[PDB]
Image 1: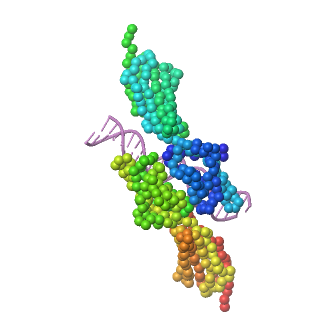
Image 2: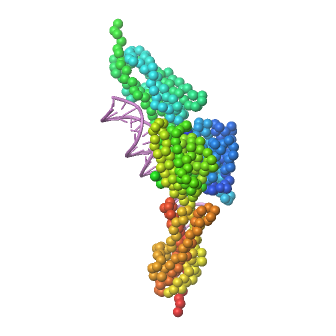
Image 3: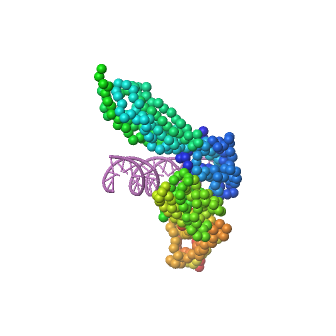
Length: 215
Length: 211
DNA sequence: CCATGACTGTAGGAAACTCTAGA
DNA sequence: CTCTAGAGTTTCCTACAGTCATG
């Protein structure tokens, strides 16, 4: 789309510009937005006056103002103004948002695990993340890839029905090669969709690898 | 205090420092502006006519949809992180308006050497703060009291808006033997060095000869 | 408890787009 | 008037410091 992209953190105010508009009223411009809150298309005016005045209100200078963002606010936003006269200008905005979960935690982590077979190593958990994002395992600071050599991950995403946010869980199990590193290091790393931010790592776990009793 | 500036009609958002981004929070915005009878304290829920002027956002930031001369003042936010954590934000606020382009009026088509002439009156409209007016001859600016060079200047504030109108009337005694096709201009040098100066179109009267 | 490290948060600077002035 | 050019304004990226967690 002619739409330019905008991304904002959840809870913070956003302010959009109406291209080529009178800086002081009286002004003629009308915003159009289809989003989570809009049933289909909501048209907003310099006067405002609906229930939207505590949500989205056109400023005296023509820009569109949102006191604090929320997930439902994701969508497209457009404006049409008249530069007198009769010059006329457009705006096309795609708006996405995000939230950052707390530092991921580990749970159900093996005191010690044994070689030659699968083991339940533990589970990472991240809460309050948007958009969803992901959990990646690292052995000694290197990546752990599924389907390959006894490495497995039991995964889910749980959306808080109220906050519309995500609770994350990743359970790792591994079959160690007999005769491997006896004190290997695992970590877990949450990453979001864009470079909207960096990566969060869990405090590692340095379990003890015990060998199988001979037969 | 952190110095701040913005255009009249523009929105303004002040970030409360060290305070929870989501409500509820414990914080206090107390300020003194041209809209205040004294120090004024606006709360999380705020209230009064102030909601139409400056309002507190769910994330703790104070906000003005349209700032005006009436709003130049002091803004302090004493906030509580959780307990009893405390950090205090401090701002100093100057504002401005860019006036209409400068104009010379009553400018001379002809003028005579050896005595004074009315060159013209450079006139600016709709400025805040008021600022200064200067003249220049063929690229270089001029000074009063030097070799028969004088100025009648004034400033006036439109009552409704509060902006300013400056008049500058230029007068000189031309040297006999100088430039018969001289070019003069006026320039508005704003109070706050926000933008570069604005200069009138030139005027190239013809120096004529007495006896 | 003290020293150390890591993080959140904020301060300053640089680059990009938009508007204004001029030909 | 359509086009060219120089600032102005806003924005993102980068960096230093304060603050919280940790050994």
